[PDB]
Length: 385
Image (cartoon, rainbow, N blue to C red; front, side):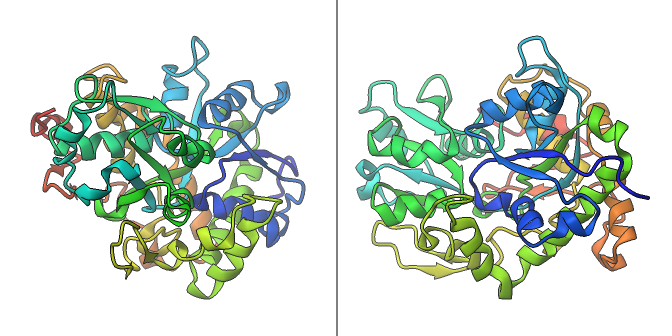
């Protein structure tokens, strides 16, 4: 029926994969579902996003957010809250693919790609080399650590990770605050276009169609306002379908570019949103529509529980979560793929576009290591570092 409330405060970080939440406002999708007063509010960092979610709207914060997939788990459990575990749900996956790992210009001669091994000897020439990611335990932290580890480098020994807000990654590499960094579009392309670094890889090269951002919300708000949560979800799904169309990419990027939103040159956004990749460092530009950010095709929006389980397993890999943590159990509480299916059913979303199972099956990483959701311990046992 009708939403219990007509407003919600949704945070986003200035990244192309926040597009569905922004387009839902700009193209009137929230209003179409009875919530024309939704606020889409830019957050300064993942740390402030976490702060505002712990606060909640009643205390001046936010009700939900475009967010890194591990965050709703770390916030619900409490590890990143300093004594304030706050329950959350994941209502949808906002996107798959589309993040980037960059290197400073000092690494140009090495022409590094998916094989990070050449960085081992190079990092040794640096006193306490840092690599930047976006939030501890978050997606970019997992991607850059996975890439460096496949290349034989160990966090705490060969390099240290540091946190830099996404919109500040380019400014930081300019002042040599780190040797390498991982962040989502549009920042990898802006790095290339400004000539302040080059790109080693786009993340769909590390894990094909990898889960990335989630549409997360405080569980108290969803449990109190189930009809409004369904309305927001349907609005986000329609915005995802809109953003996923080739014919709408130009308009999407013009909207994101505006001072109202990212205040980022259109040129730093459009090419990647079309799968056109210039990694810099003299490397020839190439096109690849399969590794670009996707918001709907290939079941991108469906929040697979097996994907959430991988993030928790990778967090265990690095010690962010206790070993043995019952990952299946917490995913069954936080992941609301059931709400996603109810919303997709209410809309059309053709049957073949609605997954029959919460697992996407075995996942294969670029180094051939595989994750079988039925045995996460075997996955960890297969990793050297």
